[PDB]
Image 1 (cartoon, chains in turn red, green):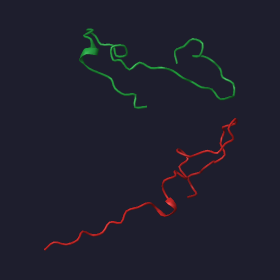
Image 2 (spheres, rainbow over the protein chains, first blue to last red):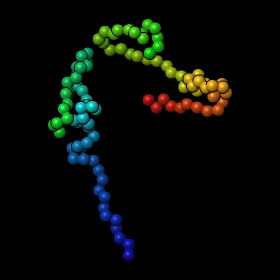
Image 3 (cartoon, helix red, strand yellow):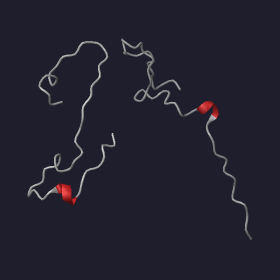
Image 4 (cartoon, rainbow over the protein chains, first blue to last red):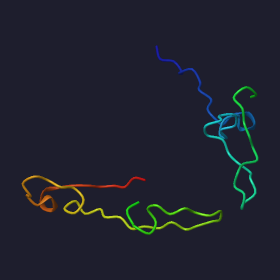
Length: 48
Length: 49
């Protein structure tokens, strides 16, 4: 007696909640003016 | 950094292009201890990054 395997849907997350290391102070982006290159996006690890 | 004119240089603010060329031949950059010629018996590979 065979049967169909339980269906896996698979796909990307809602508004891509993932791909985008938001909120990892270590691997966090930047938007600082070029010839200052200090930073403009200071990200904590509290907010999500 | 091994150059004498850059090894201890102090930089000023700005954007600079730092470029260098590496060796990936085993016989040059992998000292043995009998000198059998690595380059005939095997070696290095990447420089993955």
